[PDB]
Amino acid sequence: SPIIKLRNFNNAIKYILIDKFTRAGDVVLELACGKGGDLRKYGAAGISQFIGIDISNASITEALKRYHSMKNLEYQVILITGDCFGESLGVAVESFPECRFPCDIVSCQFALHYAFETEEKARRMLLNVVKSLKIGGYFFGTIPDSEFIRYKMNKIPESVEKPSWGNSIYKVTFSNNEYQKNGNEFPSPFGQMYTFWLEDAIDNVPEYVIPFESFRSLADEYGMELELQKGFNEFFVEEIPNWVNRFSPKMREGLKRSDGRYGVEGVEKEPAAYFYTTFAFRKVRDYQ
Ligand SMILES: Nc1ncnc2c1ncn2[C@@H]1O[C@H](CSCC[C@H](N)C(=O)O)[C@@H](O)[C@H]1O
Ligand SMILES: [Ca+2]
Ligand SMILES: [Ca+2]
Ligand SMILES: [Ca+2]
Ligand SMILES: [Ca+2]
Ligand SMILES: [Ca+2]
Image (cartoon, rainbow, N blue to C red; front, side, top):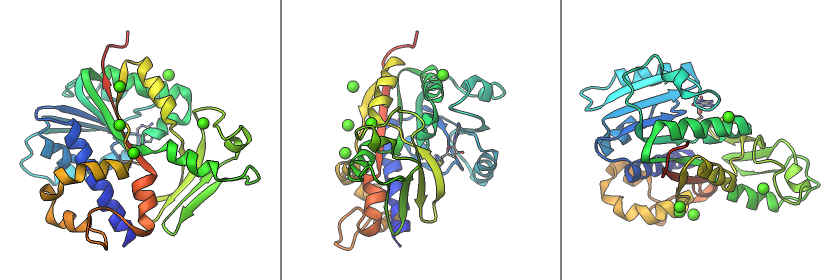
């Protein structure tokens, strides 16, 4: 189905992205790790320790259940219920002294935009990231692409009170049209809410825009400089040749279009390949 193909595609994106920035021996902190479904991707990249934190205890309980069913892992796994964005990370990790901080990588998949609820939370998130990382370490992940959101929003006239677009498997509905009323510009980088539906994945959840220019500028204030901002489509096109013969021959089959080549097509193309972007930054200096 379209949604199965979207999930396979996103998993391939994550496999490639994790391998790109993770190397043998690394310690990874995964913010907003959810149910912890990427452990084997970090394992394949050779990590020595995984630390996952999520605000949802239900998700962490499930992440722990999944982890405990695994056998003979070469790396340590620490899973913590805690707020990664609105509170200092020291609160969450105080009772887990086995965590090896500073770490080599911080990752955050399909979640960092939650930190853009307010400026306070965006800055607390960035402080948590830089203080956790070694100088030279990387911060990477996957977020809704504000540049694609702005393209869609620029095609919606100001007369529409709740700007919306979508297709048979996904929908975006903005809470207000302040963007269009403000000359097609968000009045603030923070708290710009839209409801997001993705079939069998995201049940009409309020989400916040993460304007990339603001994210980049803020990151620079905390000593992090841009490494990557390719949209999912371009990232996949460029990386899949290194990657065809490495994937699970079933995941390989799951990445095949009708025309026989690798990617996504049909109703899944827009949410899978355009709506999301990769991101990465490198910590080049200490936040003083
Ligand atoms: N302040 C916060 N601190 C930590 N996790 C948070 C958070 N606000 C939201 N989250 C988490 O953000 C996640 C968004 S869904 C993405 C989860 C996971 N990374 C995946 O790719 O499947 C949820 O697991 C949610 O509980
Ligand atoms: Ca703050
Ligand atoms: Ca704007
Ligand atoms: Ca740069
Ligand atoms: Ca780039
Ligand atoms: Ca791109």
